Image (cartoon, rainbow, N blue to C red):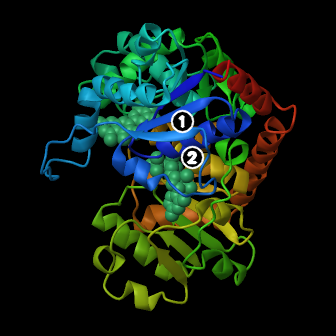
């Protein structure tokens, strides 16, 4: 047993955990194969002693983060990401040498985040297979694959939201501002250059894995499939690679048990985003005004970012936590709506939970995920003008909580949820792609 799987993870956002969970699923199934997980010290330290406390064939290694000694944030929170992207290809090669040296075995398969375009070349010089994992939706991926074409049929009118573009099958016409950032807008930051190159290199992979399921959207999925040697839909991860990890220090679930069905508003804008002060106060004031019970996963100091007295004034109406057991929250019968930024993992967890969504996208692929949930799947609505105001908020809440539209939305998300469960059954489409994925990775 000499196989050695090198796993390259993106240290930012919700990328390393899902990749690790996919890897663990594969690892337990192949106890004789060696797995090496590469990420930054910080991210790896965070990834530890979870549900699967440890797997004997998984070893973690720290890739250099590209930060200068005595580094402090000043420009933007994207600064450290850019610094990481700068020397990531050479730094991953460096740290890879440590794992080969330690295990005494050469890399046979390179599993990477799809963001790592260099995987094809790296896999080639190592005489190894390349299996990239796109952690977001099939629709955003297709958009990245079509970056060059989209740029072609795009002049000034297109860039200035004048004319729209028929970029995706079964999708509304898109406005430049709707495209995942980096495709048409700011094609200059390192992030954009990384995705652009990703789009061009993926066809070289042995197979492209994705956190999705085929029936979520047949047209997009089939279109995506024809761009790669193989497209393996191994999601939704919240079903195919779940974690026993269920932390609820603040008693969110017991708190939800004391509430009636479809009555509570769950709020979370993702792992990092912090809405602007004027939006926070508008949501705060809207919450303690419409009287909906709520659980708000807040990033930062609430006594500092929220109106004075908000906490004490709503101490019985809702809970404000620094972090919450979202997957379980969304599956709880007391939740009637999910105010989200529409990150992909949150969209999939909500689909399994069967809860209508209110979306207020901030960056990346969020805008496209909102169009997907609002105009295509119709399992959620966006807020007027894409911003949170007392007016846009109250409008979205009534539509999802007290209107017939709320029911149609729940009806559709429920059909979708069932399609997901079917894809993950013993012989479902995802279970099968997952078996294929495992074979490719461990052969
Ligand atoms: O209070 C929270 C807030 C977020 N999450 C998890 O954080 C992840 C967010 O990923 P997503 O792709 O939705 O957005 P991102 O964090 O990448 O912006 C999801 O798995 C959520 O379940 C959670 O467990 N508890
Ligand atoms: O964190 C970031 C991020 O996730 C994305 C992103 C863009 C896309 O187009 C996608 O399809 C996607 O899934 C993610 O862009 C970024 C662009 C930046 O300048 C800075 C960032 O920090 C991000």
Horizontal and vertical percent for residue 172? 56, 29
- In this rendering, the answer to whether 79 lies above or below 320 is above
Gap in angstroms between the C-alphas marked 1 and 2: 8 Å
Residue 318 at x, y = what percent? 54, 81
* Residue 88 badge: none
Q: What numbered label is drawn on residue 345?
A: 2
Residue that extends furthest to the right in the rendered view of this protein? 427
Q: Is residue 409 visible?
A: no
Viewer-closest of 348 and 22: 22
Report the disc number at residue 135: 1
Q: Quadrant of residue 201?
A: top left
Q: Position of residue 132 (x, y in %)?
A: 53, 24
Taking 50 as reference, is 30 left or right? right
Within 8 Å of ligand 1, the CB of disc 2? yes
> Left or right of 189: which side holds 296?
right
Q: Secondary structure at mark 2?
A: helix
**Residue plotted at (51% across, 22% down):** 105
The local crowd at label 1, few if under 14, some if 14 to 19, many if 20 or more residues have their Cα within 10 Å, is: many
- The residue at 72%/21% (across/down) is 439
Helix or strand or loop: what does disc 1 sit on?
Answer: loop
- The residue under the point 14% across, 49% down is 71
- Dot 1 or dot 2, earlier in sequence: 1
Determine whether the beta carbon of the residue marked 1 sits less than 8 angstroms from the nearest atom of ligand 1.
yes
Q: How many marks?
A: 2
């Amino acid at each position: 047993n000499l196989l050695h799987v090198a796993v390259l993870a993106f240290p930012f956002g919700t990328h390393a955990a899902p990749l690790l969970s996919l890897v663990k699923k594969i690892a337990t199934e192949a106890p004789k194969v060696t797995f090496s997980f590469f990420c930054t010290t910080t991210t790896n330290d965070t990834l530890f002693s979870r549900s699967n406390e440890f797997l004997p064939n998984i070893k973690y290694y720290n890739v250099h983060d590209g930060l200068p000694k005595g580094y402090v944030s000043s420009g933007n929170p994207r600064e450290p990401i850019f610094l990481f992207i700068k020397a990531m290809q050479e730094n991953f090669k460096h740290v890879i040498d440590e794992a080969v040296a330690e295990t005494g075995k050469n890399i046979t398969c390179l599993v990477t985040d799809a963001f790592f375009w260099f995987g094809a070349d790296l896999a080639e010089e190592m005489h190894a297979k390349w299996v990239p994992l796109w952690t977001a939706g099939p629709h955003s991926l297709l958009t990245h694959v079509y970056t060059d074409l989209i740029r072609e049929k795009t002049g000034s009118k297109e860039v200035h939201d004048v004319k729209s573009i028929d970029v995706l099958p079964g999708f509304p016409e898109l406005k430049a501002s709707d495209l995942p950032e980096g495709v048409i807008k700011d094609i200059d930051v390192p992030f954009a250059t990384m995705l652009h190159k990703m789009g061009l290199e993926l066809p070289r992979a042995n197979a492209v894995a994705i956190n999705s399921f085929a029936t979520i959207h047949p047209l997009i999925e089939n279109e995506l499939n024809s761009k790669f040697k193989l497209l393996l839909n191994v999601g939704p991860f919240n079903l195919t690679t779940p974690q026993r990890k269920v932390s609820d220090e603040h008693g969110c679930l017991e708190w939800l048990d004391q509430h009636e069905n479809s009555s509570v508003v769950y709020i979370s804008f993702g792992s990092v985003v912090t809405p602007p002060p004027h939006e926070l106060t508008a949501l705060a004031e809207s919450l303690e005004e419409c009287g909906f019970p709520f659980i708000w996963s807040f990033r930062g100091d609430p006594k500092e970012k929220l109106p004075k007295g908000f906490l004490e004034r709503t101490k019985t109406k809702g809970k404000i936590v620094a972090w919450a057991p979202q997957v379980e929250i969304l599956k709880h019968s007391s939740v009637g709506v999910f105010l989200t930024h529409s990150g992909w993992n949150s969209v999939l967890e909500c689909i399994v939970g069967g809860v209508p969504m209110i979306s207020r996208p901030f960056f990346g692929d969020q805008g496209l995920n909102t169009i997907l949930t609002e105009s295509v799947l119709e399992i959620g609505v966006g807020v007027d003008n894409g911003v949170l105001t007392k007016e846009s908020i109250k409008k979205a809440l009534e539509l999802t909580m007290s209107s017939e539209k709320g029911g149609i939305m729940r009806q559709k998300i429920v059909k979708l949820k069932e399609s997901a469960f079917k894809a993950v059954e013993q012989n479902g489409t995802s279970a099968m792609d997952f078996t294929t994925l495992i074979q490719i990775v461990t052969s």
